[PDB]
């Protein structure tokens, strides 16, 4: 009986219209958040994604679900951060999601009290210099 925390809102520093961040918290593994398809800029990365809860909440682990079809945007090198108030962020861990096509679970060394989590995606798979995309992002408490 692990509680899946309710994500109420989010932001993305890059998105393609119709694939904004909320498509990664709609409960549907086929619908994607996807960064802008125009990925030629030198400062395109990093791509920063923020997921917000309604209130500060206990969280023990998260699962990033990448797209299973297509290779554009599977996360690679990320910095994961959390915020107790939604404004000030603290580094939690550098996580290499490896460009993997399968879900990546990150389990914390303690229960984290957070109103928000943030992913600074430094690299991601795909055409050109790559993209960032996410089928679902999930947060859980034991
Ligand atoms: Ca989705």
Image (spheres, rainbow, N blue to C red):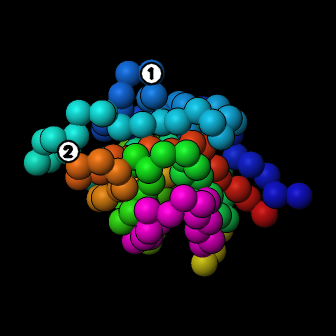
Query: Is the CB–ligand 1 distance for label 2 below 8 Å?
Result: no
From what the image shows, is residue 128 above or below residue 24? below
Residue 123 seen in the current view? yes
Secondary structure at numbered mark 2:
loop
Q: Is residue 45 magenta?
A: no
Quarter of the figure with the C terminus = bottom right
Q: Which mark is residue 18?
A: 1
Q: Residues within 10 Å of mark 2 (few under 14, many from 20)?
A: some
From what the image shows, is residue 22 above or below residue 85? above
Secondary structure at numbered mark 1:
loop
Q: Is residue 96 magenta?
A: yes
Image spot of residue 128 (x, y percent): 23, 49
From what the image shows, is residue 45 above or below residue 52? below
What span is colored magenta in the figure?
A: 94-108
Residue pointed to by mark 2? 44
Identity of the residue drawn at 36% across and 65% down: 77
Q: Quadrant of residue 18?
A: top left
Describe residue 105's horizontal placement relative to residue 89 as left or right. Answer: right
Image spot of residue 109 (x, y percent): 60, 78
Q: Quadrant of residue 124?
A: bottom left
Image spot of residue 87 (x, y percent): 38, 44
Identity of the residue drawn at 20% across and 45% down: 44
């Amino acid at each position: 009986g692990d509680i899946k925390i309710k994500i109420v809102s989010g932001t993305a520093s890059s998105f393609q219209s119709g694939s904004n961040i909320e498509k990664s918290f709609d409960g549907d593994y086929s619908t994607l958040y996807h960064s802008s398809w125009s990925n030629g800029a030198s400062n395109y990365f990093p791509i920063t994604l923020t997921y917000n809860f309604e209130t500060v909440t206990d969280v023990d682990y998260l699962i990033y679900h990448p797209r299973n079809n297509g290779n554009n945007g599977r996360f690679k090198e990320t910095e994961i951060q959390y915020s107790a108030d939604g404004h000030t962020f603290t580094k939690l861990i550098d996580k290499d999601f490896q460009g993997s096509a399968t879900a990546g679970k990150v389990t914390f060394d303690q229960t984290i009290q957070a109103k928000s989590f943030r992913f600074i995606v430094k690299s991601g798979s795909g055409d050109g210099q790559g993209f960032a995309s996410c089928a679902e992002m999930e947060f859980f408490a034991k």
